[PDB]
């Protein structure tokens, strides 16, 4: 199951992600999905302190 | 800087997870997705440079 959604993003960021898509043989939606899947992991990263 | 409004098609489970992360972070969907894209672009740049 996949959802079609609308989002507003920085145009420069979008161009970069389009290029990363091309390098990987992906279309824009697939590359964005990869980014979202990975960001879900990244937000769980932690910094110990004091 | 300019922002662009786009439509993307993504896995429903992936979207739910990032929406959950957005709520935790007090961001809206677009802000969190842009964060995901910024971080993924740097990830790919480092990956392909090494």
Image: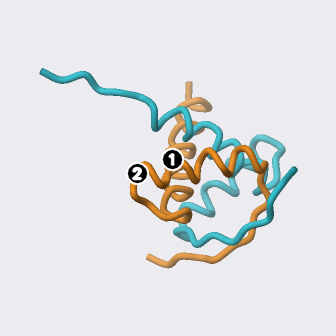
Chain colours: A cyan, B orange
Crowd band around label 2 with a 10 angstrom C-alpha radius: few (<14), some (14–19), many (20+)? few
| Alpha-carbon span between mark 2 and mark 1 | 6 Å
Q: Position of residue A33 (x, y in %)?
A: 71, 47
- Which quadrant is the C terminus of chain A positioned in? top left
Q: Position of residue A14 (x, y in %)?
A: 61, 63
Image quadrant where residue A45 sits: top left
Q: How many marks?
A: 2
Please, what secondary structure does the residue beneath circle 1 have? Answer: helix
A46 with respect to B27 (left or right): left
Residue at the spot 75% in from the left edge and 63% down from the top edge: B8
Q: Is residue B12 above or below residue B28?
A: above
Q: Chain of mark 2?
A: B
| Residue that mark 2 sits on | B25
Q: Chain of mark 1?
A: B
Q: Residue furthest left?
A: A50
Give a yes or no on whether discs 2 and 1 share a subunit. Answer: yes
A47 with respect to A26 (left or right): left
Image quadrant where residue B14 sits: top right
Labels 2 and 1 touching (C-beta < 8 A) = yes
Please, what secondary structure does the residue beneath circle 2 have? Answer: helix
Of A9 and A16, nearer the camera is A9
Residue at the spot 18% in from the left edge and 23% down from the top edge: A49
Q: Position of residue B7 (x, y in %)?
A: 74, 70
| Residue that mark 1 sits on | B21
Of A43 and B12, nearer the camera is B12
Image quadrant where residue A6 sits: bottom right
A17 with respect to B32 (left or right): right
Crowd band around label 1 with a 10 angstrom C-alpha radius: few (<14), some (14–19), many (20+)? some
Residue at the spot 77% in from the left edge and 50% down from the top edge: B12
Q: Position of residue A41 (x, y in %)?
A: 54, 32
Q: Is residue B23 above or below residue A41?
A: below
């Amino acid at each position: 199951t996949k959802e079609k959604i609308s989002v507003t993003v920085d145009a420069a960021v979008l161009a970069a992600i389009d290029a990363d898509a091309r390098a990987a043989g992906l279309n824009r939606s697939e590359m964005i999905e990869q980014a979202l899947r990975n960001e879900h992991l990244r937000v769980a990263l932690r910094d110990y302190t004091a």
